[PDB]
Image (cartoon, rainbow, N blue to C red; front, side):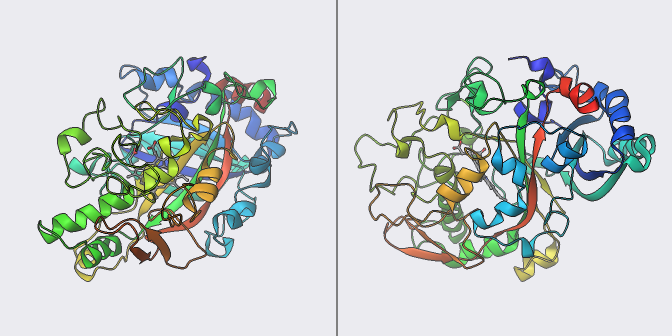
Length: 445
Ligand code: HEM
């Protein structure tokens, strides 16, 4: 795996406090290509660069192109991905949402790519934007942008709902040293043209990845109040019972401890330990896999997005089922922290959420499949009792309706909750993140 040529955000992330997603159109291909090769290609951060703390740049930069952006560059080659070529807007109905609610810019194919800028101060990002806009002139044209930031203090690495994020990623066979329980996949699941990618790619695209971007707004005070109002009756404090309902929706406590390994109370020591916090398969040698929801509901978020033993394979860790449906996640929260006024009124006023970023070699096997065939599927996982699992309580969608989620209450795996959406999609786009060599090579030719 030629790490020198792979853009850093695909495999390790930017590792910076601030990020800017700068969505652009290409107006003058000739001038754009000139500065793409002379000004962008030399500064693109690779996996090798961002892997070592020594060689981290002041401003990490990555760049990806939509289908219409590649066309605008004169690239007519088949990348091998029908979903990429049609654009995420024509795919919205697969997720039971409407482009009528999207950010107007995403509701089309006018966006030609995204520059990802990453740095520890927003001042440095603002400088690089000016620099990029002044050298490209009008050949590049900003259509939309989204500023994002790691959350402050001890909430750093947590997403807006409070849960530690970035724990579970596929390990790439031959690249990562796998952690206990982590799926182990061929490189070609993430990296186009890499080991065991079955789709033929253009040679200049070998070493890239498809980037699925989603702007996902989170209603954090609403979510916090739903947990208190629907907390399961029981022993501990009401807050503790509320946290337990939230942990059952996600499949992890806010510390990162998986409920499958500690189903009744948090354990922050476990949540922080990468040698233990993923060492599970959902199988429990004394319980029936098809009906036991006392450790983790069938509808829990992580269980719907990585089913592990719900799809067969080893009942003891590591489970390796459905390695081809793995995605690498490089998202980052956006918006202000929740304010006093919102916290006291249980109502959001300031838009916040997650800039969702998923990398995969095949969009039909990754983000799109996870969203439509698993999370939005009331009968997935299969073979359960009761068979109606319900929807993913975090990301599950059903055309704006509240979503029926089963198995969340520990006292009764048949009790249903009708849960309003706490995550609201404002849309996004499918991009191709090319290998660095293509940026000043084919894409600049
Ligand atoms: C605002 C929206 C979302 C929130 C708040 C959220 C939250 C989380 C959290 C807290 C975790 C556990 C931390 C971890 O495992 O690293 C997680 C894991 C995961 N999420 Fe989400 N997520 C969101 C959107 C999505 C979407 C749209 C998808 C895919 C369609 C997705 C796929 C996954 C996957 C694949 C995992 C890893 C599961 C595993 O390997 O066990 N997430 N997410």
